[PDB]
Amino acid sequence: DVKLHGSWVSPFNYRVIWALKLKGVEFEHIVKIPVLVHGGKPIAESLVILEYIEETWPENPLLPTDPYERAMARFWIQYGATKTAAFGALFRASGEELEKAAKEVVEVLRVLEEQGLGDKKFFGGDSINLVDISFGLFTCWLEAIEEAAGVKVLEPSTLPRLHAWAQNFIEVPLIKENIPDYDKLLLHMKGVREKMM
Amino acid sequence: DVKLHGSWVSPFNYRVIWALKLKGVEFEHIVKIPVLVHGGKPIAESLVILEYIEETWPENPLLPTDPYERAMARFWIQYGATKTAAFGALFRASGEELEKAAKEVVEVLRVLEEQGLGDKKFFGGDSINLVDISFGLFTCWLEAIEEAAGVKVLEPSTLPRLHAWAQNFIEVPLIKENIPDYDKLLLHMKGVREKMM
Ligand SMILES: [Ca+2]
Ligand SMILES: [Ca+2]
């Protein structure tokens, strides 16, 4: 009834895995992607798939009920999706350019921390929502890119609240039981950086 | 109660003008933008503002009720928002490069025509929806960019159905009464092309 055409490394595919397990939806994971196929009908683009999952299985909501709060959630999701030019530079740049790219990524994450997260445990408050799911790539995927490139970005000293969020997110049992193996993910990131020089 | 911080040329600001007039919402237009301010609270990004307007004033819906149909509408909106690298080239490129950029824009519009519009009068069926509004920049703004650059993109011969859609959209009384003056818009596009060489 529900098929997920994805991969074992893509953070975009894992956003869908999380949202489906948060709704209790059974699916067959078939390893561009991701493409969710529900009753033979396909939905592409992880952000479009997430809103489809939220509307199709409304129990245990992953977006707030208030329209202003929903607009703020979509604003932060769009903000993360737009700021990908800074993250690409972590796979291409080397030396002094790489340290400038890492500082740019930190400034992007700082806006998210100050204006999006604030003092909440999660972007969704006391539990994860679609905003947390959309920023989940900043946990073990960003950690792997940092190690493969030799640069530090998400540190407790420079981003105290976002660093504490990233630990809390990765420790959520649903997330902990559904993430790539770090060793395999790091080797994948090293290979991607090698390809893009 | 509702303020719109915008401009007289931005197609992104006009998407908001249309959606507000389709809902019968009175507002003060104050001429980055657009920023809708509702009860002192600001919402930025035209696509985030459109979903906020649709949720806040649910009468005369601008999105379908079915989740699969809503996902398809959001997919096409995201598709138009992503394919902006082809449209930028119409302001920068010259000669043989400009004709190659115009053909790339045509291929982007052809996918939209075949898979998004099909045989419907509008992307929303018998009346305009948020998909039509999001593609409204392909009407008089694209016409102005074509004239300022000396290239043809949306022609009846190469895009028969999308060309007929663009005429139908621009003739909708709500749109006809709420678009920039073509002379002023063309002079703005000529100036933007001059700036970007
Ligand atoms: Ca870290
Ligand atoms: Ca034309």
Image (cartoon, coloured by chain):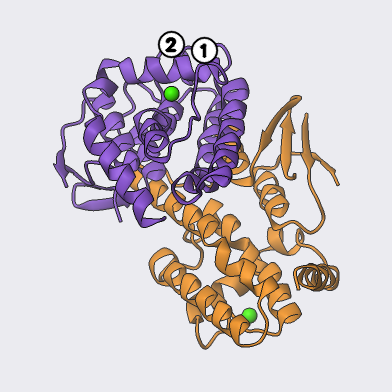
Chain colours: A purple, B orange
Residue that mark 1 sits on: A120
Task: Give, as a three-letter code, the residue at label 2.
Answer: Asp
Residue A193: tell me if it is visible: yes
Mark number, residue A80: none
Residue B187, percent from left and from top:
84, 72
Q: Nearer the viewer, residue B131 or A75?
A: A75
First in sequence: mark 2 vs mark 1: 1
- Chain ID of residue with mark 2: A
Q: Nearer the viewer, residue A153 or A140?
A: A153
Q: Helix, strand, or loop for circle 1?
A: loop
| C-beta proximity under 8 Å, tags 2 and 1 | yes
Find the residue positioned furthest to the front. Answer: A95
Question: Same subunit under labels 2 and 1?
Answer: yes
Residue density around tag 1, few if under 14, some if 14–19, many if 20 or more, within 10 Å: some
Q: Residue at x 51, y 64 (%)?
A: B122
Ligand 1 under 8 Å from disc 1 Cβ: no
Q: Is residue B23 above or below residue B73?
A: above
Quarter containing the N terminus of chain A:
top left
Q: Residue at x 19, y 47 (%)?
A: A39
Q: Helix, strand, or loop for circle 2?
A: loop
Q: Measure the C-alpha gap from mark 2 to mark 1.
A: 7 Å
- Chain ID of residue with mark 1: A
Q: Is residue A50 left or right of residue B63?
A: left
Q: Residue A108 is drawn in which quadrant?
A: top right
Residue that mark 2 sits on: A126
Q: Nearer the viewer, residue B51 or B170?
A: B51
Residue B61: tell me if it is visible: no
Q: Is residue A106 above or below residue B9?
A: above
